[PDB]
Image (cartoon, chains in turn green, orange):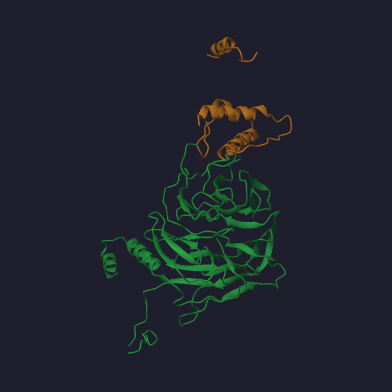
Amino acid sequence: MLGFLSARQTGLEDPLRLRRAESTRRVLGLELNKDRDVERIHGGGINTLDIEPVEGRYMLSGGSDGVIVLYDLENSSRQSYYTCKAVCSIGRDHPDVHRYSVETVQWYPHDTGMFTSSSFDKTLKVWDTNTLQTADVFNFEETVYSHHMSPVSTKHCLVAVGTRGPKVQLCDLKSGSCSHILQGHRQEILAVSWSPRYDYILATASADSRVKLWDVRRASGCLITLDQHNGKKESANTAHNGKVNGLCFTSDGLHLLTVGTDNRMRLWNSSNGENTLVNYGKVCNNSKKGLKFTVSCGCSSEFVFVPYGSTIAVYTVYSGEQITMLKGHYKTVDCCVFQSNFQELYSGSRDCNILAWVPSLYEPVPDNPAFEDAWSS
Amino acid sequence: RDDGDEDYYKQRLRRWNDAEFDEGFKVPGFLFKKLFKYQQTGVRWLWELHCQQAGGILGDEMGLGKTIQIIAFLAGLSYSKI
């Protein structure tokens, strides 16, 4: 610690070294709400979370009852153990409320004045953050399992939505569109995620055990249908061995992470599509819906936090070793988000509470009355 | 007659015997001067469809010249050897 500081002011080590080292140390020291608490307004289980792309201050949340609650995640008070209050909530009284369970929500990249929520009521809604009303409503024939917006594209505002139908739907915020549709899948599309490196590259995961790398501009099918055993190469080339219900690109976009109900997790090269043969052990996954997970950014070695039953598992992205299990929840956890600036984690589960995982090893120095054994003598 | 006959084609050959775009694409200069301004736009628009690997409908109502814009893009593609 001190050696990292001294090596910084002296100039032996580049200043990024201490930051990456201290960042990865915070992730390893993650523990429950030592100085935090999330205000509970979700009557049902919480399905999704998203931190704003800029300034990472307000966090959306979508419950199983349809209410969507926008949160505040910094200590406006002097005292510690602050409670993460909710600036606003779109509840039952709202005229434009999701009648049924809202599956995933997302902040629009490049500004915080608009956010999109998609529910099981077969609709994707565009919202105005300031006025808390809608601007565009996109109805769909089948239920909606996921939707993603490109976090890096500046030439378009396409939102990719995967429905229970076997064919991807590409809606454009600019104009209405809602007609561009990608064919090549066979069953329910449980996860869609754009590539942070390439603007027009999209990954779609569906129940036919196939993940396809698409190019939206491309007018002829898919580019790569990822296979498991890297044979010579569709109605074949199964990406997993069951139902692929997860998708998370790495920080730089060079590799793809997928989770299926085969209790297996795989890391895939983004360009060619060959799997990198990182085994990850057994990753428990019985979810029949979209499973949301995240990957750490700005650390020495990237981490991946994937829901694991009633716990969250932390793995090294490339090494594939199990770091620790964050046993905090009582029901199954379905969404986890990562606060890049502060190396904190927020977990939404089905016990109707968002848990905050904050780095430990910083404690007040006294001059603990509860920390003693009471054994008789 | 068409070039279906090899002998005929060879006979014709014996008888017979530069703007750049963003991605890198050059057209024969001796042909670009023979078209009009709108035909240049169609050639650029057609090559714009080449970058995205998507098709297109060229709906210029008759008399504007449909063959030339296809040929100029086709000839330019052969010249550039992309």
